[PDB]
Amino acid sequence: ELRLDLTAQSLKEAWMRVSFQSVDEYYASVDGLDAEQIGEVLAALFPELNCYEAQALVQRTLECISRPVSAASRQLSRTITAEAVGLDNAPGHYTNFLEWMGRLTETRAFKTEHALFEFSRRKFNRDDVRVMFENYRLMSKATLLADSADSYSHFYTVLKDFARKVAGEDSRHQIGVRIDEAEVDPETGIAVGRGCADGEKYHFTALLRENRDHNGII
Amino acid sequence: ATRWLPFVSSDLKDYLNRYWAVMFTVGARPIETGHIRHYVSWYCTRMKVVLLDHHVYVEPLRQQLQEVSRTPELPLLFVNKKLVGTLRDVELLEREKKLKDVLHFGFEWRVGGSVAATNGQKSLMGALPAPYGDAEFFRGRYRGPPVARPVVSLPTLHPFA
Amino acid sequence: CEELAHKMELMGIVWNANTYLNLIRSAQVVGDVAAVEKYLSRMREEGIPASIGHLTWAVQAHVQSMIRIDYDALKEKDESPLPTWLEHLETCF
Amino acid sequence: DLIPKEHRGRFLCNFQLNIVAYDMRVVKFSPKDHRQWIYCVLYVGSGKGIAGWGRAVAPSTQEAKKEAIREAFSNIIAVDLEQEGPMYPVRVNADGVRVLLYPARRIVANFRVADILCAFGFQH
Amino acid sequence: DTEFQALVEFIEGASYDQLISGRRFKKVYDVLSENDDMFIWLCHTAMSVLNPGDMRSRLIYNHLRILAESVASGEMTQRTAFRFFESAVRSPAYREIAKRQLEGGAATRLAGISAAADVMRRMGLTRRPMSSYFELYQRIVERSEAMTPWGFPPLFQFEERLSLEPRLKFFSFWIPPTWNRAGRFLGPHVTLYPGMTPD
Amino acid sequence: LEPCTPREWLQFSHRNLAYAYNGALRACHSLPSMLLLYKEMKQRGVKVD
Amino acid sequence: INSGDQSPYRYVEERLYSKPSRLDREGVKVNKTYALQGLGDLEPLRYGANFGISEKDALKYETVAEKAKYMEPPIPYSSLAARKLAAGALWPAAPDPEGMISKE
Amino acid sequence: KALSPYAQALRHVALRGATAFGPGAKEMELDMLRKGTLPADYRPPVQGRWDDTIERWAYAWQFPAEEEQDDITKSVERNASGMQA
Amino acid sequence: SKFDYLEKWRDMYRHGTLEVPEGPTLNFGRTPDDHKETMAALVRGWYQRNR
Amino acid sequence: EKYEPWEHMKRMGRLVGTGFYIPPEWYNHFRMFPPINHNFQ
Amino acid sequence: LSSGINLGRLRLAEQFSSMNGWQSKEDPAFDAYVKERRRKENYEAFDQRVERGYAAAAKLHKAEIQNAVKRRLKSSGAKFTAETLREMSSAVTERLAWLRDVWAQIDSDYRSGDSARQETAAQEISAALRGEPNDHMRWVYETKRELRFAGPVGRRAIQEELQAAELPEVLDEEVNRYHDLKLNMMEIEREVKAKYGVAGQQHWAELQAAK
């Protein structure tokens, strides 16, 4: 994916070095270059590159004029299937819709409204509520009026961290065990730990050292 | 208006056209028929069970069943003239909660994704497309609750259940 | 009649000289020269040309408008309808 | 808010009300508590074609009347007063109560039904 | 936004009380979930499965469009709208059209739903300027009416009675009074429904 | 969030904050946006993983 | 939940499925028994807003036959109904078969 | 009102003022999207092929049906020489 | 049609054949004093047409 | 049968015909595009 | 019976039944129809936010016209007939076209690029979305009542002054509806206390003491 994206960007910059879209051209989805042109230039400059990879480079270069990464459609293809959407013998229409839907899903309004949906579905905890309260508190009145114009900005400024939480396995924090820093005497390299039991009856402090030899005793 | 007559036909298609949900079985597989009966009766749908052991036209009906299901498996269920399959497929549909609809309305949800695997209410957390992918290269990604697992098999309560 | 024409539009049976003629006649029977002129303007802004029948029924809308004006409410103001009659005859000729 | 939303900005006539009956009714909430609510049935009429009848239960007379009026406006109906009444006999049977409505040149019903006919506007 | 005000009140109250309470979550959830989006999406999903060429389909399309516009503007109430909708859906012509559609390999249903989302945005039938598109994503990726073969949710109120009888054994929708021992709280005043257990 | 009470001090840790900052970086959509977050990571004592 | 002199299962049963619980949910002032607040998508679809049929209104009919006569049809669909459909909760999952094993 | 197309166009240009001849709403949305300054309020004009498809559907619900294309009796009527023979 | 005339004028403006002021000259409905602004914007055209 | 959409249309027709009720837009729109009838086919 | 009409609609049925025959280059007739539709759209179409504001304003104006006609009927005791319905609809359509041109001005300003013009368009769009009614309409109502109550030379002066302005047709009922509704006291006290401060508080204290 990185190879294809960077090659597409290199070709786009080459075209701009060498050289606005109208409504008719936008509807026709005709970019500054043609698929045949991209294929010929790629075949000329890259001999060993295979036919399938050349077709992939053509597709990616054509699509990077609209969206650089556009990795949402590839993933959404697995969630939504042609038969499910009733579009089985129309692969072109299926892919067109998948691109449309992924590029719409990537939008800020879509994330805000998904976060609102999950909040309505009650998948937040007191920590999330506190974070939302801090965001709202730091948000000011003039900023609130400014964001009310967009009508999604003020929602997003409050739900931004919860927007991360709802996107679970790709962007969710994992609160792991606490990892502190070592505390050992530099001269003698001894670490001191504590232990208790029975409240006030049993109390021990253990001094731990690294036995440079393999003869360690307690 | 006419005397009662039990229905018989040498064609599987007659059974499919006549009965909504029809299961073909034998007397040598009582447990599978009992399980499919349990599921269908739980979902309260009229169902006809036909025993092929004494049914006349046994060989015609058997070969027709085998060619339509692409397997010799006598306990077979049919809804809307389609094949839902044997007890294993019925159990699968019960697992992912598509059996209610395949019985009542006669269609399997093709939405993709499982509804059985849920921690609470059903929502879309983790469904949105991930930019650039790389759901695996966030080693400190949220991993979920600490699922527990058994140590030994805890012998099965009954050889059937 | 108006809603039948609107249903033609919404069902995709686009309007025609005959449809506009029907609308003009419907407006004329009550004497709505305003609606008749609006219908003629709609025809003109569309591609269809208005015809001598449409002009005839515009003149008929004018005669009905002359008939329909409220002479009691005009008398209570003490206003002669002669200027209105002359306006109508001027536009028709 | 007494008129439902679907009928809010549409009535061009002033309605006038009267109550068919008030009553005392006991309502059970739990086997250990029975409350004593009030039941009211009433109807509203405009005297020019639009009228309706509602009924409700509430712990108070005013609350019951409010709910009954809301139901009456929900179940409001209409007639045609070109002739100020019917033009043929209408015989209906609403599960035991058999009612005849016929044309005339006056009101030929008892006072209770004459009030309803006035609510509707049926003088003939 | 009123729903923004509700969210603000909920967060304020939860942070004040140091707990998330049933009352306040109920208030915010109701404010969030009070909207006619469900019915308008129902109606437009039904409209989607139609064919833009058939004249009967055009009549049904315009009828359902008028229905959705009326409910959105609030002129007609939800119950009356559902009666109109269930009639227009149970019609035989609609079922013939949907059955014809589901047969082909390339059905215009997806385009129908997308155009429905765009129309909802433009006509202002939504709660926020871009809510219809998340609604569409949900209807596509989650079990809804957009994923059924007919375009309406899988209930027996939207099915044919003649189609209802031969499938499920239900009678021949209240608990008979003679059944004094049915359940802990089940009684004759508790209703039942053909294809669902709302409990 | 800055730890104020001992209960939050029992949860604060730089290497663990690296997790939250990685998550925010992944959530971010633009390199210019991630630059401010990474500059703040470095300005803080957060351990870079 | 806080359970006093009764099991939590029976306590939740009373506070979910019960005449006073339903009446309080519809908004009728009762004191001894209360419904469970703010259950999101978990409250029974029978008692969700815009579904079923109002018990505050149903109090108005003295008999079940009268209720059947005068009671208008229920709303077929709702937002909570859509959530239940999406979760697959319109019909309980089938329990293990008990009609083919003996009683232990 | 009763404005002819000429006066209607003149009034249109009077109401706009040299912006009527500019790019247009869709073109400006496209330019904002490509430059990255598109408010979240706006529907992004993206995936032109699918957008055109759905718009074609929307206009398809109004598209008229061609009626009475050709009549053989009228054709026979029209050709004078054949009818004379 | 209005749109045919308007497209031809678009082409003329693009070619520089005709000149249209930047911003609306006939303006109304937005402020109480707007016909005055329209007159102020049309003075030049009216005087040139008359003389 | 009391709740049929045709009966609702008729009831609204009588309400609007009284002359003291303001019709909704959907009344005229449904007069143009009446409900879909199951009968006669 | 398979006539020209029936055959035409039968032929139109299947191409749109499928998803194939009505695409970008399949049916030239449908392509021309869509081209004309888009040609009209690109000219008569506004920007999205201005469209939303226009929708809100049009809703308000529709409601106000309907309220005016309802006021006429309630006052005169007449009954709402089909003639009244048609007059209502025609007036609403006229007002919608007028304010459509008004928001054409607004959209052109919003798209001009000039910072001040875009600013003004932004505040007016925001006001329309928040639903605050215009001040131009208030001035229109005030001027209409003044014309109603003015003598003959004053009427001629104002009428010839405004005849070219193209102001919307306002019903006497709508003007009277605007004028009749009472004026709030809290806004008045706030405005006087803001414009005069301590003098405003002293005056309002005197007024309340009078109360």
Image: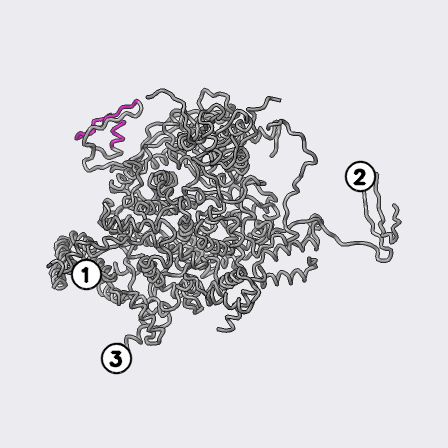
Q: In which quarter of the image is the C terminus of chain D?
A: top left
Q: Left or right: where does residue A147 sit relative to residue C19?
A: right
Picture layout, residue E134 above or below residue E95: below
Q: Against B127, is A6 above or below?
A: below
Point out residue B88 in the picture as x, y percentages from the top left corner: 55, 35
Horizontally, is K151 left or right of D53 in the view? left
Disc 2 designates what residue? Answer: A199
Pinpoint the chain carrying mark 1.
C
**Do callouts 2 and 1 point to residues on the same chain?**
no
Observer able to see residue B5: yes
List x then y, in percent, for residue B144: 63, 45
Image position, residue E97 (x, y; %): 35, 43
Q: Which residue: 50% across, 73% down?
A: A18
Crowd class of label 2 (few under 14; some 14 to 19; many from 20; radius 10 Å): few
Q: Position of residue D67 (x, y in %)?
A: 39, 34
Span highlighted in magenta in the image: D96-117
Q: Which amino acid does label 2 sit on?
A: Gly
The residue at 37%/33% (across/down) is: D68
Comparing labels 2 and 1, the label whose residue is closer to the camera: 1
SS label for mark 2: loop
Q: Do labels 3 and 2 share a chain?
A: no
Q: What residue type is labelled 3?
A: Arg
Q: Identify residue for label 3.
A: I51
Give how far apart the Cα atoms at labels 3 and 2 are. Answer: 109 Å
Chain ID at mark 3: I
